[PDB]
Length: 158
Ligand SMILES: OC[C@H]1O[C@H](Oc2ccc(-c3c(F)c(F)c(F)c(F)c3F)cc2)[C@@H](O)[C@@H](O)[C@@H]1O
Image 1 (cartoon, rainbow, N blue to C red):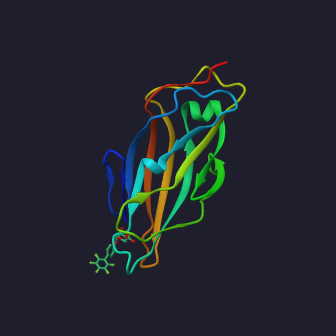
Image 2: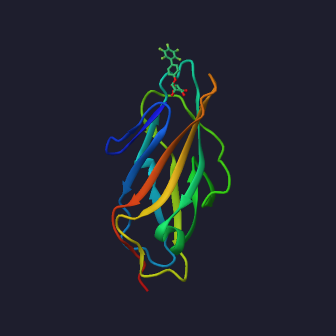
């Protein structure tokens, strides 16, 4: 089991950490959602699916910078929504293909009334998402750390 980003940065077998720089909707009005869809940014595969089934959870998701202070929201993992920042590890998703497939994670964030104009600053850390991988084969328990950075400013107009 291993993963890569959209620009080709890999976290190999055994886990690790990587930085992910995502483009964000530059304008989010009150009432709208800011969607940070990592399923187009993070991909993973199973290295021997005929014998081994890989299990993959979102173990923890933390918010930082303007996402912490200016938004309220949730994380959607494989069709289910949970609080964000997370309070517990999600259920497992099955990976059973050698073809790199998306990690189905997305943040759904809406501005709080006290949000400031410049809600997210370009280049800032906005989230840390931990992918935890196990299997039905041995005792492997590996954490893939995804550090999410904003590519651009996000403004919430009045
Ligand atoms: O994604 C599958 C596994 O890939 C790595 O662990 C491997 C253990 C065994 C084999 C393997 C196998 F199971 C076979 F049946 C083979 F024929 C073979 F050549 C293999 F290399 C490949 C990867 C780790 O990330 C682990 O954590 C993961 O579960």
